[PDB]
Image: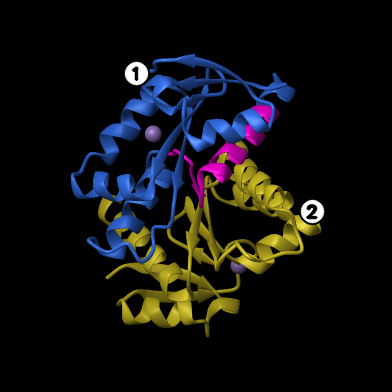
Chain colours: A yellow, B blue
């Protein structure tokens, strides 16, 4: 089976439930950065669409990505939930943030519609990491 | 204004119409690779959700990304349209492809819901490129 380190704050999430159903072996830790660690280089940050939008409003998104990159050489951000129909911010603000993180900071931003899908992504990434290690 | 080179096959698309409304100055060329060129390093490939799925079915997606990377150091792929509810392929096949391109090949995959949104992304990326040149 594949092994993934999970931050304590994620322990009782539906993501963890699906990872367990998928047969993933989890090791719990309290991480200063990241939510799911796949390898010494690959770490995943789970962020809801609402929190992404809030971090854009408060201008804290870039500091968050900076911190991720300084801790892991190959960080990944999974944005969970729909970003559409969510007012309180012009679409260009969301688009601009996405483009900056993925193209400028060079941090992949994979989109997931549910916690189950976030788990499915974590699982397939970890499986590939294990196979090529 | 910002300047973008557009491949001839895109000339009469709704993407081009919006780019023109946004004030972008377009130079038409027949490109061997890429759909919208922003700089010597940044090129954008527009691909509909249906074509993305088809390229996964036919196993041609990776060759396409390879070709993009060999032509431009900083290529970007904009997937246009929803990938959900589109059967004829298991979700893991789509997820796996997305993860491979963005994390392994290191090519950003920005998602757009419409040709207008694809244009909005092209515009903001080009504007930033111009400002920092
Ligand atoms: Mn998180
Ligand atoms: Mn295209």
Q: Is residue B43 left or right of residue B94?
A: right
Q: Which residue: 73% across, 60% down?
A: A55
Neighbor class of circle 2 (other Cα within 10 Å; few <14, some 14-19, many 20+) is: few
Q: Which mark is residue A14?
A: none
Q: Locate the N terminus of chain B and report the quarter of the image it occupies.
A: top right
Residue B59 placement, left or right of A14: left
Furthest toward the left, the residue is B58
The residue that disc 1 covers is: B32
Say which of B2 and A32 sits in front.
B2
The quadrant where residue B119 appears:
top right
Question: Residue drawn at (42%, 46%), measured in percent from left and top?
Answer: B103
Ligand 2 visible in quadrant: top left
Residue A4 at x, y percent in the picture: 41, 68
Count numbered badges in the picture.
Answer: 2
Residue B90 is situated, as x and y percent measured from the top left of the image, at 25, 64
What range of the chain is rendered magenta? B106-128
Q: CA distance from mark 1 to mark 2?
A: 40 Å
In this orientation, does residue A16 appear? yes
**Could you say where residue A95 lies in the image, as x and y percent from the top left?**
64, 47
Viewer-proximal residue among A27 and B117: B117
Quadrant (top left, top right, bottom left, bottom right) of the C terminus of chain B: top right
User: Is B31 above or below relative to A115?
Assistant: above
* Secondary structure state at the residue bearing disc 1: loop
- Which residue does the numbered mark 2 point to in the structure image? A59
| Residue B91 part of the magenta-drawn span | no
């Amino acid at each position: 089976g594949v092994k993934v380190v999970v931050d304590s704050r994620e322990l009782r999430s539906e993501v963890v439930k699906r990872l367990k159903l998928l047969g993933v072996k989890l090791e719990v830790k309290t991480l200063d950065v990241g939510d799911y660690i796949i390898s010494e280089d690959v770490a995943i940050e789970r962020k809801s669409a609402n929190d992404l939008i809030q971090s854009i409003i408060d201008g804290g998104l870039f500091d968050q990505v900076k911190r991720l990159k300084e801790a892991y050489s190959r960080p990944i951000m999974i944005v969970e939930g729909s970003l559409y129909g969510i007012r309180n911010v012009h679409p260009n603000a969301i688009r601009g943030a996405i483009a900056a993180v993925t193209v400028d900071f060079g941090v992949p931003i994979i989109f997931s519609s549910t916690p189950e899908e976030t788990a499915q992504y974590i699982f397939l990434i970890a499986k590939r990491e294990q196979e090529e290690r």
